[PDB]
Picture (tube, rainbow over the protein chains, first blue to last red):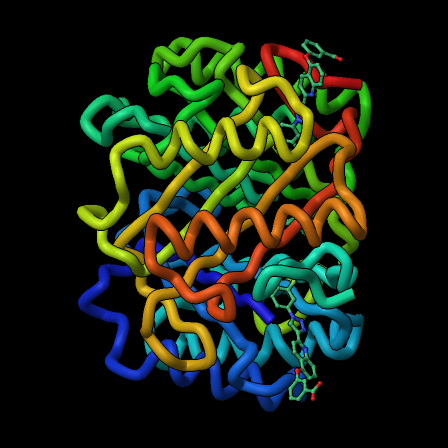
Length: 114
Length: 114
Length: 114
Ligand SMILES: O=C(O)c1cccc(Oc2cccc3nc(-c4cn(-c5ccc(O)c(F)c5)nn4)ccc23)c1
Ligand SMILES: O=C(O)c1cccc(Oc2cccc3nc(-c4cn(-c5ccc(O)c(F)c5)nn4)ccc23)c1
Ligand SMILES: O=C(O)c1cccc(Oc2cccc3nc(-c4cn(-c5ccc(O)c(F)c5)nn4)ccc23)c1
């Protein structure tokens, strides 16, 4: 899986270990092996939510399967929880786009997963 | 909705009020409540369009509904118009990816919209 | 087409000519005209692959057509090869999301491609 979070929170508020924490939690939530989970945090961004510059986050999770109604609700609770705890971002100022990707549309290691 | 614009235009050349203007314009164009519009501008980027580095922009709009043939044509004119006036980027050096997202695939406030 | 690469490799390690190289290698791989290829490189990123912060890259390619099983395998070999050669990133730490976009959902030059 690939997880990306963009936020207006400064880099200084991103703790040591945050990328590992995201990796960790996503591995268990998805049941995917952690060595295949990529994570990307992008702080200090010029962004607004509802026209307000208070802390917010715009995120994506791409996965081959393990994407669905109930699963995405559980990921949103998990990710909003972490963003609130570690970055002090209110859950109602977080958006996450989920993508169930076809294996043929994911490149890795000179090939694709199909 | 979520709107992102990535550009090689420098930060200092992004005029003040730009995020608020995008927020309001996207609200009226989509008919979505402005409270729920998120906008993100990423200046100073290392990018090329047709292999040249004159000003350009790479954008995306995600929405649950309000996406379609005629709407996307209208959005593209509106957004290219704004980028041209504010950031001085020619419309022929702007791309916008539109995504009609399923409510189940959009996380927010500890849950999804489904 | 639109190609984005985000990496933790430092900006100084991105060769002059890299954006041009991407543009023309993709032009030939996809058969799309290079004047319509947009490329975006984002160095110095906070990211991990498998929880490790060794060099890695997270990429996407959006195109109207020229996306499929064999083509995407070929693009992956090509892009991993380029990233290995120029950025010294191992192919097992590269991910590429491929998107076959509907022409109605790609904005350009005040309209869409539909
Ligand atoms: O075949 C084996 O022996 C073996 C042993 C250990 C691990 C292994 O790899 C895997 C096992 C199970 C699910 C796996 N899922 C993935 C996987 C990767 N994605 C994924 C990554 C990035 C994206 O941008 C994306 F859209 C999807 N989604 N799932 C990769 C490897 C897996 C395979
Ligand atoms: O339920 C209510 O009582 C109520 C009252 C006031 C406002 C309200 O919120 C809404 C009303 C109508 C459409 C709405 N659409 C959205 C909405 C959000 N997206 C959206 C946001 C981010 C993305 O990445 C994405 F793919 C889609 N697309 N639509 C949010 C709130 C809405 C709901
Ligand atoms: O057919 C047209 O409407 C048209 C109009 C003007 C020029 C033109 O030149 C072309 C000839 C052949 C393939 C072409 N492909 C493209 C093209 C652009 N994309 C493309 C760009 C960015 C994206 O984010 C994306 F999802 C797709 N995918 N294909 C553009 C122009 C082409 C094509």
